[PDB]
Image 1 (cartoon, protein in one colour):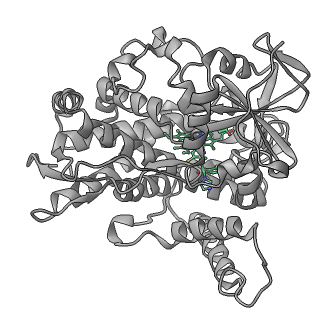
Image 2 (cartoon, protein in one colour):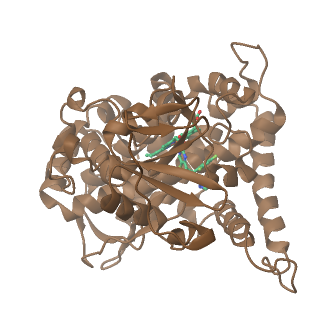
Length: 456
Ligand code: HEM
Ligand SMILES: C[C@@H](c1ncncc1F)[C@](O)(Cn1cncn1)c1ccc(F)cc1F
């Protein structure tokens, strides 16, 4: 029954120039602040409706009426991730097949089995910071990415990236980032000329080969191994579908490996980085979290059971995900003609985009203090209405890695708070870099050891 707001248009380009910025999600949040709970965004040949209120998003999350959509971003990265779990349609046969095969790799029982290898990498992080000299500082997102990449490599695939042995990032992730940048930049401007893009397109082939060589090696080293593994790669290679009784095909396996290597570390690094940012900006909250870590983590290394008792650290992480969910949007399509919210008619196939940071600032849900960092909002999880808090997506297409991410992040943040005091020595000004995920660029701290020993 109502007509939808729309931001500024530019002739035949429609709204597209508004995203000529390196911070498009933050630009869309500002449009949502100006225009409200829903607005229409048009580009040449596509329309998207952006949702920001829990009132409308709770309906969008009704899986009888809306299914996951492959947004323009997911259609773009499908060039690399193929029909892996993140980039396949719900009704593409390999989605449910791979979901069925890999679900058991993300249970609590699987988490108990990953714990010792998560501790392996977390101890390496703590030892790096213990070994810094006087007046040296920490590049926070850089070291969080070292940890999370190593953790998914070791836990998932028994592969050691050995990121803490490197002063620059592992070539695999440099090659991935550079291949994606090149693929993006290429979508514009006189492409077959003298240099083209890659110094005549050679660097992309090299970067593609880096990624294919690593996938080759992860698979070959497993098959040649005379040790028993039971990890994510075991299920990828050998798990049979409970429905059809067949394993994943070889091509899809390659896509799942690169999907999980990337999905399994990037957003978790961003979460750890934002959580430490908010802690040093809210020293009362840091103190409360540090007291919990000291009281709970009484052993030289944490046990799985002790990580489960880091209740306040978990609330800290959820509140960082509330303010800056590091995968900040997900996309849905209308299965049939329908009316959203009693007021906005949709046609079959219409795209809805959930603007998660704005959902998480809905004052009718959280109160007027939405910009404050207050972990106590999560003291009682049953008090949060359904579909108010969605940093991991929705329904059967929600993040399969959610518990892995939160166990890793709770473990590591707990050990950080046990072993160091933290100083915001530069009075860092939050600068949020946007790729397909969010991170606090240039965030640096100093860590003063509490001199607490690590069986590390
Ligand atoms: C705090 C960290 C993380 C956040 C915020 C996050 C966020 C998300 C979101 C929002 C989705 C839904 C995407 C969509 O609807 O298009 C998703 C799906 C997915 N995530 Fe994550 N994720 C995190 C960590 C992880 C980890 C650690 C892994 C792997 C170990 C992972 C693997 C996946 C996969 C495979 C899917 C697709 C699930 C499916 O459709 O079957 N994510 N994640
Ligand atoms: C969105 C993000 C993600 N999704 C879900 N859980 C964690 C994440 F970290 C991402 O890593 C983004 N990304 C894309 N190319 C580089 N990075 C991603 C990973 C794999 C993928 F198949 C698609 C995809 F969008």
